[PDB]
Every structure is written in C-alpha cells, then in structure tokens.
Image (spheres, grey):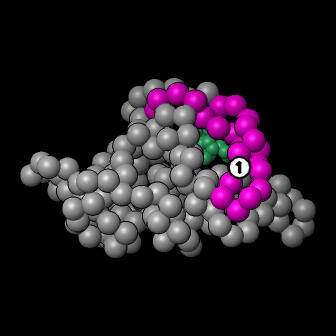
Amino acid sequence: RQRFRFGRLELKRISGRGFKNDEEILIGNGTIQKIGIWDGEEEFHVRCGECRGILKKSKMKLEKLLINSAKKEDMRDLIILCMVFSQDTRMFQGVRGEINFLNRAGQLLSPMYQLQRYFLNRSSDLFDQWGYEESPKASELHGINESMNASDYTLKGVVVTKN
Ligand SMILES: C[n+]1cn([C@@H]2O[C@H](COP(=O)(O)OP(=O)(O)O)[C@@H](O)[C@H]2O)c2nc(N)[nH]c(=O)c21
C-alpha cells in the first residue's frame, strides 16, 4: 500500500481494489473520449499540501470525502482533485470548455491528468455542476460550500472534521 501521486494529489490505499476498463465517456463539452474507468470500491488516505483527507470511490462515483480542516486553498484543491480522481459522472459533465488530449507536437496526453489540469483552473464550474446536499446534523462534522466556508449545505459527499 505505498504512497503515490496523481499530480498534485497524493494517495495511499486503505482498502479495496479497482479494475480498469476503457470506456467511451461523453464529456460535458459534447465530445466523446475513451478513458480508463475504474470499477471497484476503493478507499484512500489523500493529501494535497497541508490538507489531509479520506476518500472513498466506486465506479464513476465519489462515495465520500472526509477532510481535516486546513488552509482554504489546500481544502479546495484536495476537493477538486478527489472529484477528478473519483471519475464521478458529474465531474465529466462539468467540463464545458475545450480539452485537448494531444499536445502541439501531436504527442499523447493522459485524459485524467488533462482533467486535473482543466479543473484546478475551473473549480467554480465543477462545484456548480456537482451540487449540494444538507450538511451533517452532528457536532463534530460540518458542511463546506464553494467558498470553503462552514455552511448548512455541503458539496455532495464531502464533510469536514476538526479532530
Ligand atoms: C495504480 N493506480 C493508478 N490510478 C489512477 O488511474 C488513472 C490512470 O490514468 P492514466 O495515467 O492516463 O493511464 P491510462 O490511460 O492507462 O488509464 C490516473 O488517474 C491514476 O491516478 C489508480 N486509480 C484507482 N482508482 N486505483 C488504482 O489502483 C490506481
């Protein structure tokens, strides 16, 4: 279970096993792109900068992300990166602009890394497409909105702890 990266995101497996299959994904800008889609419930310690979290995913779905509160920019990037890494259907649909899967020399680019790069610059569109649900009714857990503020609605599947 060794530490590994997905760009700015760092992960370490807690549980589960994924199996990858290539699928044709309809992305939110109207294009269809072939992307390795993971199947399986998997769970990971995650990190971005000084922000720690726990992520659970299943096929094309962020099941849950529990983050330990931290500087806001690092909370926000951790959230964006977990949305991309979960391969959630809503994340794909959130892409409204152009995305290239070849560079200017005609070289091959990673669809997932390209998504990461796209969304770290377009998080408002992502949060807007992703949506909100009621925050937890427990004292030791709080909701978080698009501004990384504690709120009565939280990004779906995302909760913050101070413990
Ligand atoms: C080894 N390991 C790699 N990743 C991710 O899967 C994606 C691989 O995408 P890629 O690097 O473009 O390779 P590919 O086109 O051959 O599919 C990246 O986002 C990796 O972070 C993985 N993702 C999951 N869910 N489970 C894993 O065990 C795992």
- Residue 31 included in the magenta stretch of the image: yes
Q: Which residues are magenta?
A: 20-42
Q: Residue at x 50, y 61 (%)?
A: 129
Q: Is residue 149 left or right of residue 95?
A: left
Element under disc 1: strand
Give the image location of residue 151, x and y in percent: 23, 65
Which residue is nearer to you in this view: 118 or 74?
118
The residue beneath circle 1 is: 26
Which residue is nearer to you in this view: 151 or 3?
151
Total number of numbered discs in the rendering: 1
In this view, 100 is above or below 158: below
- State the residue lying farthest toward the left: 139
* Corner quadrant of residue 18: top right
In this view, 50 is above or below 20: below
| Residue 145 visible at all | yes
Which residue is nearer to you in this view: 139 or 82?
139
In this view, 136 is above or below 24: below
Q: Residue at x 76, y 49 (%)?
A: 33
Q: Is residue 143 left or right of residue 110?
A: left
Query: Magenta: predominant secondary structure element?
Result: strand
* Corner quadrant of residue 24: top right
Give the image location of residue 27, x and y in percent: 68, 54
- State the residue lying farthest toward the right: 106
Give the image location of residue 46, x and y in percent: 41, 48
| Residue 12 visible at all | no
The crowding category of the residue bearing disc 1, from other C-alpha atoms within 10 Å (few below 14, some 14 to 19, many at least 20), is some
* Quarter holding ligand 1: top right
